[PDB]
Image (tube, coloured by chain):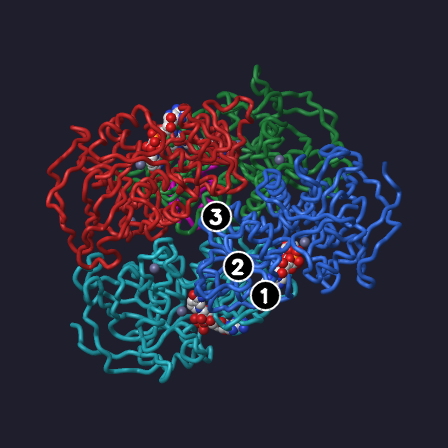
Chain colours: A green, B red, C blue, D cyan
Amino acid sequence: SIPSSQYGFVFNKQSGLKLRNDLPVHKPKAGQLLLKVDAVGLCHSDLHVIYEGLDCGDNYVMGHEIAGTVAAVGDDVINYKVGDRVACVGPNGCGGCKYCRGAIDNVCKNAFGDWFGLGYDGGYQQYLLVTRPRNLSRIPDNVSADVAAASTDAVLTPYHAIKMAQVSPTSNILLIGAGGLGGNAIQVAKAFGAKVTVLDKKKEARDQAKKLGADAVYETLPESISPGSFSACFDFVSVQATFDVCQKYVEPKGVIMPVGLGAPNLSFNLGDLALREIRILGSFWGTTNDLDDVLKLVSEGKVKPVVRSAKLKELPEYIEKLRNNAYEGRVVFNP
Amino acid sequence: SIPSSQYGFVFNKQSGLKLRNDLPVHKPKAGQLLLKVDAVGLCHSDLHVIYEGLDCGDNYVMGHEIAGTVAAVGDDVINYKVGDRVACVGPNGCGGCKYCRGAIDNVCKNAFGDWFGLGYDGGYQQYLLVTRPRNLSRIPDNVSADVAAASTDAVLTPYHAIKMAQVSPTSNILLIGAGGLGGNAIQVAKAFGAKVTVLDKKKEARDQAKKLGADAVYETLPESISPGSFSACFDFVSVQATFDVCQKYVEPKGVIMPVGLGAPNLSFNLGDLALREIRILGSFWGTTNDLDDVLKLVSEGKVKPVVRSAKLKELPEYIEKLRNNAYEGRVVFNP
Amino acid sequence: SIPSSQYGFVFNKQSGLKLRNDLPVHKPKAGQLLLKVDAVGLCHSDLHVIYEGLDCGDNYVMGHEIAGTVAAVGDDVINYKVGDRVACVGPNGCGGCKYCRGAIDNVCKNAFGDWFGLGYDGGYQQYLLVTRPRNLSRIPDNVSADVAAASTDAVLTPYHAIKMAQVSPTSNILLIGAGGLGGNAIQVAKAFGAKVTVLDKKKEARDQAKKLGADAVYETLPESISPGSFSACFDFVSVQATFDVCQKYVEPKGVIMPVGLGAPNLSFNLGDLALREIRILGSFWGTTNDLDDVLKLVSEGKVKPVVRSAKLKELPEYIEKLRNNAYEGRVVFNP
Amino acid sequence: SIPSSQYGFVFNKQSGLKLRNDLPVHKPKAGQLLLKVDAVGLCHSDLHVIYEGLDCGDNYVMGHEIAGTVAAVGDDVINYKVGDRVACVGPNGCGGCKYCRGAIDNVCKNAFGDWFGLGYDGGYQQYLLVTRPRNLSRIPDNVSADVAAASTDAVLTPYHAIKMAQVSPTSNILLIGAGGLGGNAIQVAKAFGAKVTVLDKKKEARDQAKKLGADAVYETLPESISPGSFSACFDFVSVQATFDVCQKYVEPKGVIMPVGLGAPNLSFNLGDLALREIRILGSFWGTTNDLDDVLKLVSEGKVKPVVRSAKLKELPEYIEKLRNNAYEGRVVFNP
Ligand SMILES: NC(=O)c1ccc[n+]([C@@H]2O[C@H](COP(=O)([O-])OP(=O)(O)OC[C@H]3O[C@@H](n4cnc5c(N)ncnc54)[C@H](O)[C@@H]3O)[C@@H](O)[C@H]2O)c1
Ligand SMILES: NC(=O)c1ccc[n+]([C@@H]2O[C@H](COP(=O)([O-])OP(=O)(O)OC[C@H]3O[C@@H](n4cnc5c(N)ncnc54)[C@H](O)[C@@H]3O)[C@@H](O)[C@H]2O)c1
Ligand SMILES: NC(=O)c1ccc[n+]([C@@H]2O[C@H](COP(=O)([O-])OP(=O)(O)OC[C@H]3O[C@@H](n4cnc5c(N)ncnc54)[C@H](O)[C@@H]3O)[C@@H](O)[C@H]2O)c1
Ligand SMILES: NC(=O)c1ccc[n+]([C@@H]2O[C@H](COP(=O)([O-])OP(=O)(O)OC[C@H]3O[C@@H](n4cnc5c(N)ncnc54)[C@H](O)[C@@H]3O)[C@@H](O)[C@H]2O)c1
Ligand SMILES: [Zn+2]
Ligand SMILES: [Zn+2]
Ligand SMILES: [Zn+2]
Ligand SMILES: [Zn+2]
Ligand SMILES: [Zn+2]
Ligand SMILES: [Zn+2]
Ligand SMILES: [Zn+2]
Ligand SMILES: [Zn+2]
């Protein structure tokens, strides 16, 4: 049956993220549903929230890569039934604004500060109350919870960005960072037919980037590669040093995608951006529609997320390891 | 008759901009044509180059807003003939690469730095040798040399940016700076149907902005105006302070156009740009096709450039005035 | 107060459109609301349903240009309150599908056959039950019901089409038909900044087109006009003769918009369409977001719908006049 | 050495396509070059010209899929050298109009009726005079002349259309016709990552379609496939019946690409195109930039044109087999 209480990690600004053993298990009201978390991923963004002032709100269960099984549905829920395996659409769009009707519910202003695991409660618990079921994607039968969870951000974000940049078979792109996101960016990009060059400061990540399909992998681009030669540069790190590499190597009218959140601000050379018409396109998570596209690509085997799983109570240990860039790929937790 | 020597203003990194009374006038070889300058405009970019280290080559006659009359055509040229009134397409693209064949001849790599008045010789002289006649647009009979001169940049640049921003009747835009480019941007934007709000530190510029069609003008945007409510923000100043205004007032997925070149670098808030998918689009001058459109808009009266003229030998006195923001609109010179 | 029974014109396949005196006044369930019709427009499409046997469904109150005031809201409805003046979004999207969330709720497969007044009940009655209020747009205070009504189709449709064609100040377009939609297409197009040439076989319509802002109006295009010289051709008639005019005068890569529905099938010259890459884009009504864009353009005075009002009971007399192209612009009715 | 006379096939409205053993060998004038034809392909289009009067001009050497080696260069030709292996860009744009500058040199008006082998002389000869060298693309060393010839149209045309339709990894497309163009369209579509369904009346073609990578291949779509379920429908046949299939199976807002020229006219159901906003996009050959993209994709092994070669003098025989749809893929000839 479904318990009266549960354990989970709650984030509070004065105490950080804390394990709580006596959390309530909400019973879904009309239009809501209860999701039993099967897998929740750890995104590097949680590190920015907890340790670097990335402000998303206060006192909420973290964990935004959520995959679970419908455990209970409130009155009026007809689209979902207990037993349905689903993954959460991070942005948690309101569903009624011009954004949520305009194919871009990821930037819904009403939902700003109310994202799953980033403002609103997330997956670092046993039972998640979903107030808006519209923000759910059905997980295909052949896709595991662990992979589905990673798919909601580690894959979704790169997919959304790559789609936005309109990558194609004539694309010659550069990806900076081959971690959780970068690793899936490689596979998504290859699916679009692009040539992919990867940069990463960690040898292990570089080795993995190669196994995943990257056409070229380096720690530092050789002097032999020409500046202003890439059609698109996706920066999954976003510190000034990496942004500078993108601006140097992107071709005229090419695009720079600062997906990474490694700094509060970044500067660009104005004379260069203007005269060569470089485009800096912000990209955030992904849309409800994108998620459906994504789970389909994973299901069909085009994207295989590097995932490793562990018990949810081991989370603090893995956060520490992540802080030290001590592992490759993604790690997901089973509550 | 065509003289064998001329006067003009030559820019050198060591001696700045200097008047030369012994510049050479060369009959055009095959493929080339000699243009007699009728009007050449003074753009603020010239101030950046002469006084602020904006790197635009060395050792060439300045003046990049050029309108004139063909004085001689080399053999092989059959697209133009003596007497034709034409305006120069600044970027001076090679016309044979993938950029030039791809509707973006303004970002041609082969020709990077080979720009009229900003790398290659320009209009601050009596005769300009044009080596690539393809980079000329016919001036309509009812458009004066003075107006056509201003149109090649002051009107062309903002037209190119607005067009790139896909401005429309549903647009709510903010323009910062109502000088040479700004005043014309107001008119172009109104032609596209946008609502225009202008910011300028100088009363005279605000008044002109208003006379030209701006819906609202201010020295300081009222703090009560909702942040993130403009679909596009065109910054024709580009210093850190104005860029910050753009990022604060641009709506989600909206666009920031840093057309101005007032600083070597500009920084943007990373979390804001990413989470709200803000776009920063570099825009440079205009294309050959763009200029034809611009000259048609001007001939039709949709854009009426604010212009006043003087003898080219008065350039020094006007450079100082523009440097002190002493006049409104554009100033053009007649050699 | 709210009456128990009402009058309205119900459409049935056996007996056509007949006036009823015993129509119930539905009490809105949860999530629904009751709209008191203040103004309802007569569209030419209604004639296709009544006389050309255009199958939209059967046994429903017609009238799809709807404007009114909220008379009652069921439980749960909080986005609307009795007294709110709103206009119906014709397509009546379901809201949950990928089309409705994808910025294109006008083609929602789920709501096919359930559009206001064209499958589902409409505005040719006193009180309309609104099952899905997401399909409503608030009417600005300075916009009358009568004008709002015409805005939901007469204006909305050509707006949506014109926007799709990406018209701009460089566009040279041709519109065929200056009636309900045509007259507004003229205004919306001028707003977009395009030069507009209009064709209409009726002098009174040509006279009005000129008054509305058309740059040139004719019955037949003069020989002086070159073929393939229009960037876009909007056909609000759509019979083979008018389509032929479009394909002959549209320029290479240009677009033809068969907005009109005057024929079951139309043919195009394949050789011409392929070699000159002509585009034929289908356009249907408008989206919820389009209507907000539209009502705003009207409130701002950019579009002044030629509207004339009469009492709903006079509908029959007016349908006959429309059948005979006896009047110009739109006629809307006050219940 | 270069002979003073040659043989080739000339088309005339009166005598049809006839072999000539006394054709002159043109000496290149300045800016022009002579090309030694290494391989020329037979496109079904040639049949329409010979037998069905698609009138492209008169008295010209046919054969528009051209690959060869520069035999001679006139004075001033600098970008090309004797011995350079190049493939002709069919449309043979003028290079100086707004279309050629606007990334669409394939619809250049000045060049209408002056295309390689279709108005202007083509490849069914030994030495072709190229009056406009801009319409050449370098053949990579690892691409044979036979394959390159096929790439100038059999691959280029479908590449252009597929690029235009913006196919992607989430695309579910239908291709009708698996001949010369069809077979390559399958390969190009896969490189873009789309799911492909092919239709061909001929068994051998279906069998080849399967070997080329189509996900599903049929003679007739099984009743188990839902109408309006394809994102894009490419018709490489274009007879009323195939178009009808496209209109029935394309999903809302989907696109129909009538690339085939199997009929002088085609009709579309207006009610259906309008309500489901179906798009019909004309597509013609390819652009100079498209060919560079294509030869690169071929060189990279992503597209392997099914090609079989024969002596040019055997052309009369193969034209007959093609009329009889007797062989699969493309057949190219060696002069
Ligand atoms: N824009 C969005 O919507 C969005 C969504 C998810 C994550 N993110 C951001 O993306 C970034 C990465 O997420 P992640 O989970 O993949 O982190 P990760 O820990 O899983 O992987 C990080 C990788 O970056 C590499 N790296 C770090 N600094 C580098 C440098 N200076 N040069 C080269 N390589 C470097 C590391 O070696 C590591 O392999 C984070 O900053 C996160 O906040 C953004
Ligand atoms: N991207 C391009 O291709 C391109 C082409 C031309 C010019 N530009 C750049 O555009 C900028 C303006 O060109 P211009 O000739 O119009 O300058 P201008 O001197 O003709 O007009 C400048 C205007 O900006 C206003 N202004 C200055 N600082 C301001 C501030 N902090 N806040 C608000 N308003 C301010 C001034 O009062 C004045 O009205 C220059 O930096 C120039 O280099 C760029
Ligand atoms: N696609 C859509 O979503 C949509 C929405 C509404 C209406 N429509 C269609 O648009 C068309 C017009 O609607 P309306 O209410 O504005 O019609 P209308 O009666 O209000 O105006 C019709 C005008 O077309 C002119 N006209 C008719 N035949 C002509 C011809 N052969 N040549 C030149 N001019 C001609 C008439 O003189 C008249 O001025 C109808 O066919 C309607 O079904 C389509
Ligand atoms: N628009 C352009 O720019 C362009 C460029 C080249 C060719 N084309 C046109 O494309 C068409 C095909 O060119 P091609 O060289 O590939 O022809 P092809 O002879 O090489 O191959 C034709 C294929 O179509 C199949 N087919 C014919 N009728 C069919 C039907 N009713 N249903 C299903 N399958 C059918 C045949 O079995 C054959 O496999 C021609 O009409 C040609 O004119 C257009
Ligand atoms: Zn994340
Ligand atoms: Zn929302
Ligand atoms: Zn300038
Ligand atoms: Zn170039
Ligand atoms: Zn209607
Ligand atoms: Zn829907
Ligand atoms: Zn062909
Ligand atoms: Zn041309």
Query: The disc numbered 3 marks a residue on which chain?
Result: C
Q: Residues within 10 Å of mark 3 (few under 14, many from 20)?
A: many
Q: Position of residue B334 (x, y in %)?
A: 24, 39
User: CB of residue at label 2: within 8 Å of ligand 3?
Assistant: no
Q: Secondary structure at mark 1?
A: strand
Disc 3 marks which residue?
Answer: C168
In the image, residue A181 lies in the stretch drawn in magenta: yes
Q: Is residue C220 depicted above or below A325 in this figure?
A: below
Give whichever of D1, B16 is nearer the camera.
Answer: B16
Q: Residues within 10 Å of mark 1 (few under 14, many from 20)?
A: some
Q: Are marks 2 and 3 in contact (CB under 8 Å)?
A: no
Q: Which residues are magenta?
A: A171-197
What type is the residue that disc 3 sits on? Answer: Ser
Give whichever of A124, A48 is nearer the camera.
Answer: A48
Disc 2 marks which residue?
Answer: C256
What type is the residue that disc 1 sits on? Answer: Phe
Residue at 86 percent across and 53 percent down: it is: C20
